[PDB]
């Protein structure tokens, strides 16, 4: 919301998990027994970046 | 980096479309050569 | 359900390699595509 | 003998010629096949 | 017309033939050149 009031351009379609990780990395994360959950995927991105 | 590949990939396809256009022109030219060579050879066999 | 998710995971993986490899083929070929018949065969196999 | 001498050389030449025309026919066959395959490749690469 | 029909086919066939013989002549030329070059290589490799 704040970026909108500041006229800072950002896309509102792509999810944060898709923009911060690739499908190849998510495939390996599943093989490592990471639960198929968006919050769990967000945690994996944090554990990498 | 992605935009670099797309521009190269697009330009190779566009060049390819040009190549077949002249190759079809070459194909027509080679057909004309066959017509000339075949006609010249037949008249020579006739003189024979 | 479990088998399909494994199958669909591999299938989506393969398509990503296929679009990457096909892009690489056009980004690493010199001159024209038609000149090297190997590049033409590789594109057909990747497309197939 | 003067005619057999005219004919000999001329016919040898026309055999060299019709063979040359036949060789070009193979070249045209290679060209036309390359046109169709590259056109099919271009049609297959239309989506990409 | 029956003779012109006999002759047409036979002469087309003999043109395909003399062209085939000429193509083999190129093959023999490639073979004989390969013999001389490999023999010279063998003579050059005699000391080694």
Image: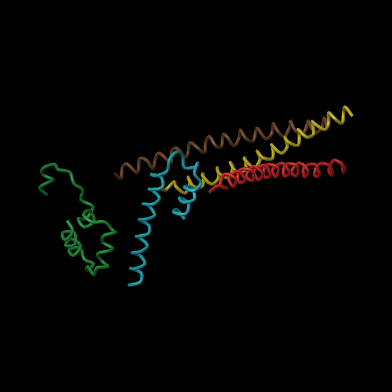
Chain colours: A green, B brown, C cyan, D yellow, E red
**Up-down: is D24 above or below E45?**
above
Image quadrant for the C terminus of chain B? Answer: top right
Image quadrant for the N terminus of chain B? Answer: top left
Q: Residue at x 72, y 41 (%)?
A: E22
Left or right: A42, with B9 as reference point: left
* Relative image position of residue A26 (x, y in whole percent): 26, 61
Left or right: B13, with B44 as reference point: left
* Relative image position of residue C34 (x, y in whole percent): 50, 42
Q: Nearer the viewer, residue D7 or E16?
A: D7
Q: Nearer the viewer, residue C41 or C19?
A: C41
Residue found at the very far right of the displayed protein: D1
**Up-down: is D30 above or below D10?**
below
Q: Which of the 4 image quadrants contains residue D3?
A: top right
Q: Residue at x 11, y 42 (%)?
A: A6
How many numbered dots are placed on residues in this image?
0
Left or right: D43, with A42 as reference point: right
Residue found at the very far front of the displayed protein: E47
Q: Which of the 4 image quadrants contains residue B12?
A: top left
Left or right: C9, with B47 as reference point: left
Residue found at the very far bottom of the displayed protein: C2
* Relative image position of residue D27 (x, y in whole percent): 62, 40
* Relative image position of residue C33 (x, y in whole percent): 47, 42
């Amino acid at each position: 919301h704040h970026l909108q009031q500041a006229n800072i351009q950002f896309r509102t379609d792509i999810a944060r998990t898709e923009y911060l990780s690739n499908a190849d990395e998510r495939l390996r994360w599943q093989a490592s027994s990471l639960p198929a959950d968006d919050l769990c995927t967000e945690n994996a991105i944090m554990l990498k970046r | 980096e992605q935009q670099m590949h797309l521009n190269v990939g697009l330009r190779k396809i566009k060049e390819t479309v040009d190549q077949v256009e002249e190759l079809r022109r070459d194909l027509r030219i080679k057909s004309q050569e066959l017509e000339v060579k075949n006609a010249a050879a037949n008249d020579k066999l006739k003189k024979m | 359900r479990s088998d399909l998710l494994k199958l669909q995971g591999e299938f989506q993986l393969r398509l990503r390699q296929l679009e990457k490899s096909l892009l690489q083929a056009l980004n690493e070929v010199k001159g024209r595509i038609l000149d090297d018949d190997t590049i033409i065969t590789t594109l057909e196999n990747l497309k197939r | 003998r003067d005619l057999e001498a005219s004919i000999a050389r001329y016919k040898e030449e026309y055999a060299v010629l019709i063979s040359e025309a036949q060789a070009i026919k193979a070249d045209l066959a290679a060209v036309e096949a390359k046109v169709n395959r590259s056109t099919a490749l271009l049609k297959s690469l239309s989506a990409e």
